[PDB]
Image (cartoon, rainbow over all chains, first blue to last red; front, side):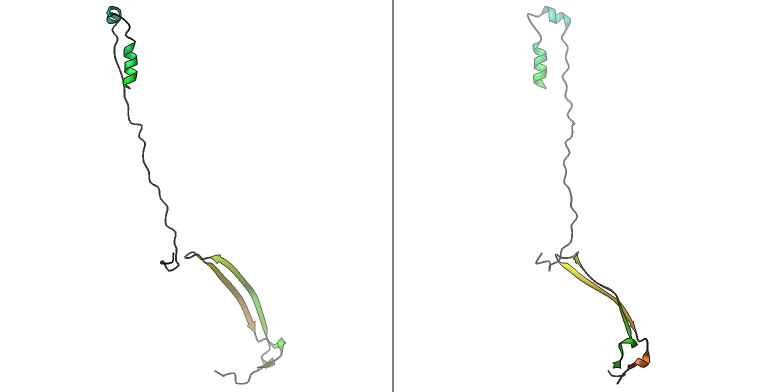
Amino acid sequence: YKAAGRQTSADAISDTGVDLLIDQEKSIDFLVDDIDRVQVAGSLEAYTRAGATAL
Amino acid sequence: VAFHPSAAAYVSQIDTVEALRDQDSFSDRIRALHVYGGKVVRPTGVVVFNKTGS
């Protein structure tokens, strides 16, 4: 203020900005065959848990 | 000037002072206005020596 004589004037205020884009669309999609569900040695539920773990 | 008070008239109509803030600096601004007028209502009742003086 002292170097500017003793003068002042109002500057315009402003913003900065960033955009959070909700732009990631990811999917899991698979078949459990009715024949294989009978013919395998045990449960196949583990593929649903593995699909959820991949996402 | 030799005269009688009743030979001339004066009106002060506005006599005001205000404070403001300066737009260009951190200051008060003090301003005052005076609005007024006057007339010699009877010219023979005012007698002037050296009226052309200065």
